[PDB]
Length: 468
Ligand SMILES: Cc1[nH]ncc1-c1ccccc1Cl
Ligand SMILES: Cc1[nH]ncc1-c1ccccc1Cl
Ligand SMILES: Cc1[nH]ncc1-c1ccccc1Cl
Picture 1: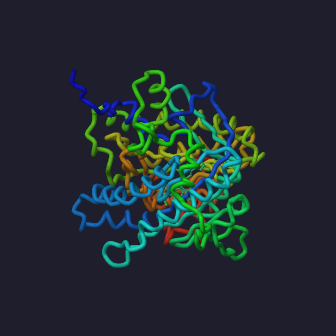
Picture 2: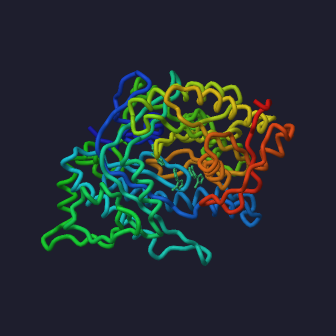
Picture 3: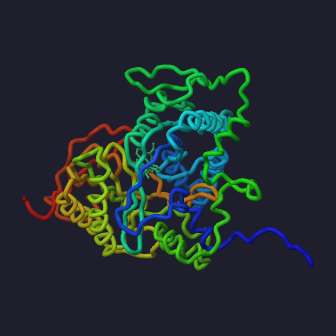
């Protein structure tokens, strides 16, 4: 008999799994929300610095109304190469957000030393992709990489139809602090990463007024062979594609239909993405430069390094946030947590073809969230930034590992407003002026220099309907 070969791999469950890390796809966990798990690993935070400041360039008339299409194409061309490097080096891409991605190598404590060496090699090869690269003339296509290592907690929260996850703890905070110290072309190790690494492998230098270090070179011993070393490291990589599947970037490409697994995984993915996955919407429909209102919510914690306290508090806040968003068709696009602050990137006005009073409603939703979350046990401070304008929306990353993302100066502005103006609901000039709400509903604020923002315009606190 004939033997026609090659397994069919294009099932809905496989398409859904592209939107998720192995941490979730192969997770198998409890029905309870919140769910918490604890492990050790190495984290890599890759920032494509300056990229957002080039989303605004693609709004110009020169792109002839194909700005969003050209933006997603060039971003994915470069980000796909970074993703492929991470995946071939055995990493799990956790999330894409803003200009960045975060990857994880989960391993037992005893293997952390050797895995750091793998992750440094990976980081150097990523830099290597961009060594002789630009577009017009002064294009700064270079990345900044922070690495951290140590204890990691995962939190999964949500309701009967939606799930979200976050990674938490000192290694998570450290990786963002490390990437923030990086200049273009740097690999920065967190203090704990430098403490746990194989110091015979690397030459470092001190970072002024910091315990983190910069990697100058990976200079391995005379008898060292990276390929044979990496092979030894794969013993500890549960899902590294191997044997008959050694030609694949992810084991998740091999997932077979399983309705119970698909029910769990689809909860993490927006309904408009599922519509595209199901071939009920055109594959290009979600790449757009679209006017939206960003409502960026930050929850700061009492018992701040305490994962077992923060989990219930985030779940309780989430249950309220999702009810408020439902009424006015808002969406949670991203959640992430650093420096004991859990942030929700909420968006009013993307795939859906309508919403009339987007601004008064966005402000009222922000105040509702603010009032409720302020009364949640263990939540110390709630801060909300509200900004409105044109943002890029689209699926970013590699065919095998990508996520819907929102990118733009107004997203960065709302993020910076919630950090620089803590404990209040703030809005930009577009939102203030457009709402047509009486001026006494607001307080005009002092202008702050915000790292990353070049002229915010006037900013306002949304004071609310009453003096009290
Ligand atoms: C840089 C950027 N571009 N678009 C969004 C962002 C962002 C900035 C700070 C925190 C989180 C995010 Cl997502
Ligand atoms: C470095 C970066 N680039 N784009 C977004 C970010 C970021 C910064 C602080 C916290 C969270 C995020 Cl995602
Ligand atoms: C999921 C998460 N929890 N804490 C931080 C993050 C994160 C932040 C920025 C980019 C990617 C990720 Cl995974």
